[PDB]
Amino acid sequence: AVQKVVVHPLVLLSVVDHFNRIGKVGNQKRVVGVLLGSWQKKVLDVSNSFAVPFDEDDKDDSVWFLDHDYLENMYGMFKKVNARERIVGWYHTGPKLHKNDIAINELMKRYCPNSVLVIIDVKPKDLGLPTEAYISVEEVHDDGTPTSKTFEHVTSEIGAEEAEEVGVEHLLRDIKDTTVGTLSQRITNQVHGLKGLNSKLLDIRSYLEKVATGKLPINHQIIYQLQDVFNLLPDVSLQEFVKAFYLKTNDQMVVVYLASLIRSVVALHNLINNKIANRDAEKKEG
Amino acid sequence: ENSEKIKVNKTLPYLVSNVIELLDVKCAVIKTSTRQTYFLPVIGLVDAEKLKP
Amino acid sequence: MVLESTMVCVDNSEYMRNGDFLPTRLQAQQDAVNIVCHSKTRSNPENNVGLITLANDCEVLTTLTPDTGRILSKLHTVQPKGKITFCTGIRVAHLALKHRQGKNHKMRIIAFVGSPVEDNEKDLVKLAKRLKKEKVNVDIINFGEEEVNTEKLTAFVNTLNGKDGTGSHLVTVPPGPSLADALISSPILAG
Amino acid sequence: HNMSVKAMRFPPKSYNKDLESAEERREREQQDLEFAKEM
Amino acid sequence: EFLHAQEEVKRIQSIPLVIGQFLEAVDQNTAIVGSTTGSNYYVRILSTIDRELLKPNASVALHKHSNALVDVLPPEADSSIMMLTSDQKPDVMYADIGGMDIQKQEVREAVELPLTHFELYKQIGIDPPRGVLMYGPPG
Amino acid sequence: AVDTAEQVYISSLALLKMLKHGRAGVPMEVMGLMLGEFVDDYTVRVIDVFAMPQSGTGVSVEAVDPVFQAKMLDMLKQTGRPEMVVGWYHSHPGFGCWLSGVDINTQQSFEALSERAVAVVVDPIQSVKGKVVIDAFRLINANMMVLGHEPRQTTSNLGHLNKPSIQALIHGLNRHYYSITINYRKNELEQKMLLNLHKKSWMEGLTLQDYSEHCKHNESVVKEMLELAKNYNKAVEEEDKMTPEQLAIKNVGKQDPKRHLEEHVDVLMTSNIVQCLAAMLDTVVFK
Amino acid sequence: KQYEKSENDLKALQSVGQIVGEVLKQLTEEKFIVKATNGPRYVVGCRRQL
Amino acid sequence: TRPANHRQLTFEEIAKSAKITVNEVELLVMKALSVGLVKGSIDEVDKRVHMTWVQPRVLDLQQIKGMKDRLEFWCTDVKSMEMLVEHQAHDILT
Ligand SMILES: [Zn+2]
């Protein structure tokens, strides 16, 4: 299907504004709308979004309303302002992927035959990216239920347009990884990556709590992947692998050695260049 | 409208130019008497057929 | 008049396609709406109608819209197939009122019951219970020759109008081929 | 290299006040041009 | 904030610019450039322009309102485009020339050979010809 | 009787819409309506902005369409929250920030319906990284100038903080219209959901970047220092001569090994430090 | 009937001319080198739709 | 059954457990690999068969508890390597 879905900052912001605009109830309620955007070379881009009215009682989650006329009427407005953008999917806060959001996609399947739903939290206090993009994929089997239809995840990242980036960076003026070198990498990928790995691993452990207190009767497939995960663990570091590592870890140190030595020489010449400067100035002065 | 129409013409000083190519993708390309070319999208207050290159 | 908004609740059950009135209970339904939607309009030149299917699940065709022709045309291609889920049907119409146009329109929904109705009472009282809480009166019209007098809705409608709550009323039709015509007059007259 | 930078911050001493060309000349010229620009 | 003043001075670049020409640098922070409108202007160079590109006569972009170096464009041209094969190649072999070996050899030894075997000329000591005239009867 | 402390707060989101629409029609002058709420007799705050369809060819803001205005306004209310049109914005591609003759004429129309309407100009080309360039404006009455009495009745040193742009001053700045200070509202939920989201990655940290290609990159870079270093020797003897300004100008046509050599060294040390470090970090995380 | 015809002319008084030149090179996606066929060489942008 | 560390099934150790002669186990391993059901290589010098990936199967309720152990012993190892960098790289952060 689609390899990845890029979400522009404007759409991200128009969803936070939507929740606060209607979230006067306070306790809890999702918010659902319709996404707009365009894609090229099998890579989706989402730029604009508008709010579609949507209500649903909590009990017996098979009741909900989405205004088709509002979707059709408003899209006539957005089409006039910008013709390039056409409906591509829908969004909803829905932190936990509520169950009823598998027949809703059928409602929006009319306007976009291959639509994607992006769940974007409005109240994020976490470390991961707050944009999960799912696509509908169909396959019926004899294990789950006679009617089988499940979402498949597509990697999503926050994009940036030339005009939006100007505003986005102006709006922050709060913190930036200035001098983006060894300092940002040691923190933007190494430490953060470990944090994510732990959380995902902890997520797996939480599900495995079913061993004692069964929640679902062994999903079967989840176990299959977990078995493959363990086999894929790098082979014990005791064989010829250890020699290969040293022959490469040390090989990288020579370049570091050479780079440092060149750095010292240039640093020493720089001090000489400056030191002779003030000595010459002082000598002439007195 | 005539009051507004005369207002543009009321600026009597015109800049004589020679029509270069009466393109039909009913537009006109002119060459003012200052060695400047242009692409007037709308011909203006003149017929599109009375103007020959 | 009185700035009313009605949200029609159409029926398309599989046993609803038998013609015991004249052109089967599909044209009998289509003529029935025509004599109400136009009747629903023409009093206040700002009204609103919406047709909702009572098929297996949430099936809504046209939303809150002042136009009149959309509903009629949208009624076609509504060939009946399946069972009727009344209990979860009104609530869907219920939400449509909540997300309405300018809220200064009085809210009501006329029901178009039909092929054998299914309910367990008790819950129906709760179904009528909530709607009667929030400035809502429903209009279930007995039709399709359900059990005589439909003594399951009887415990339903009275709940809304209970405590001297004058409003919409249950309307029944003879099992014989009684043409729909203006026979529907209890709600339109004064309720 | 760390030591080298250690002696780098000593040399700077009273070397910041260095006007490029001048101050009065630029200001006077700008004011005259602005007055004529309006009319 | 230094990183913020650097990203704020770029406003002087802007889209609408007039391509000029670099003539000579008078001192650091200043230079002499020639505008395509036809003139020679004394402008001030931006403090972020890599001076390594400030070569002899080259392409430099000047601010519209007040001429001032704001970029260094890659080399280009207007009425001279290299022949990119396609249908714009001559389509004539050396075997289609009616036996002009002596003339054919001379052009080979003065144009084609130096480009390929450049290092040989230095080794022998000859100075490669720097342009060949082709004069003769009409046809 | 204005208060010369208007301080039109715009948004953390209305600005992005203004810029996106401005850049979309960069050659032309797109126009739209601002949906904000008056709060004080001293401040006017905008919350949301929606665009108006372009009439067609022509770089102008000639007129607004009444029917389109109503249709969208009557449609946003039923889902969002009611808002009243407080001003209109049109994007100047690269001219600057001011009001032209047509823009002034269109502006008095809005002021007629609403007394305190605010006109905004957004420039999508001049704004680059940290400067957005808006400079919202408003009209001054011709009667006052005929009367000669200065308007805005300044009662605080708040409006005279931004020096008017000379380009804007050439036009009817402080003559046919007066600028109003513009600031922004920012909250952590907005910021944390934008700053901590824009440039991030999920798992790229523990990726060893094509170990075969890594050393090849090192060889090419290091080999460049072999020739670069040699030119460094030739760049030290001829230096430290008379007229260093002459020396300074002498480095305007030829690569300077002093800076070029350092640039390569910087990339070399970080690439291996990161690349090497991930090697040991991975060797413990996975078995 | 003539009033409608006159209105058409009034709809053309707001359309201005455009300088004519030929593209020389494409520096980037939004930057071009164009020489107006009267005078100097300019680096100018490009309309998104085009 | 064998832990991933050893996985050095010898030719004899396979024939005995399947009732084949030593001079025939070779066709068995290829048959398994041909279908795509196990992955590995065959070394007919020391008479060894390497296995690297046996197709996953079902684990009723006890081998899944053991799977929990291998995640606890692994989450805690990754946890330690996180604070190690965070503590010795306090200056390089934020
Ligand atoms: Zn304007």
Image: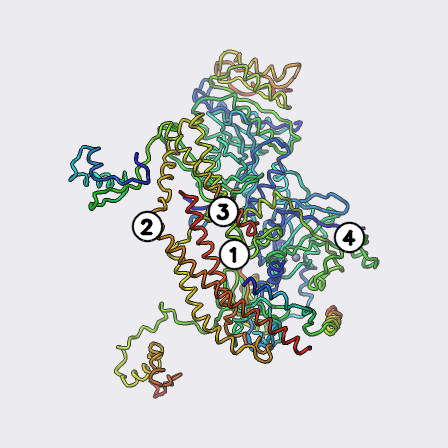
| For marks 3 and 2 on the same chain, the one whose residue lies earlier in the sequence | 3
Relative side of F108 to E138, left or right: right
The CA distance from mark 3 to mark 1 is 22 Å
Q: Are marks 3 and 2 on the same chain?
A: yes
Name the residue that disc number 1 marks: A181
Nearer mark to the viewer, of 3 and 2:
2
Ligand 1 is found in the corner quadrant, namely: bottom right
Q: Relative to A251, say whether H42 is above or below.
A: above
Name the residue that disc number 3 marks: A157
Q: Are marks 1 and 4 on the same chain?
A: no
Tell me the crowding category of disc 2: few under 14, some 14 to 19, or many 20 or more residues within 10 angstroms, Cα based: few
Q: Relative to F54, say whether A103 is above or below.
A: above
Screen quadrant of the C terminus of chain C: top right
C-beta proximity under 8 Å, tags 4 and 3: no
The CA distance from mark 4 to mark 3 is 44 Å
Q: Which of E76 and F221 is in front in this view?
A: F221
C-beta proximity under 8 Å, tags 1 and 4: no
Chain letter of disc 1 in the image = A
* Labelled disc at residue A114: none
Q: Provide residue A112's location: percent of width, then percent of height.
A: 46, 41
Q: Provide residue C79's location: percent of width, then percent of height.
A: 44, 27
Amino acid type, residue under disc 2 in the picture: Glu
Name the residue that disc number 2 marks: A240
Name the residue that disc number 4 marks: F4
Q: Nearer the viewer, residue F257 or D21?
A: F257
C-beta proximity under 8 Å, tags 3 and 2: no
Question: Does mark 2 have its CB less than 8 Å from ligand 1?
Answer: no
Chain letter of disc 4 in the image = F
Amino acid type, residue under disc 3 in the picture: Glu
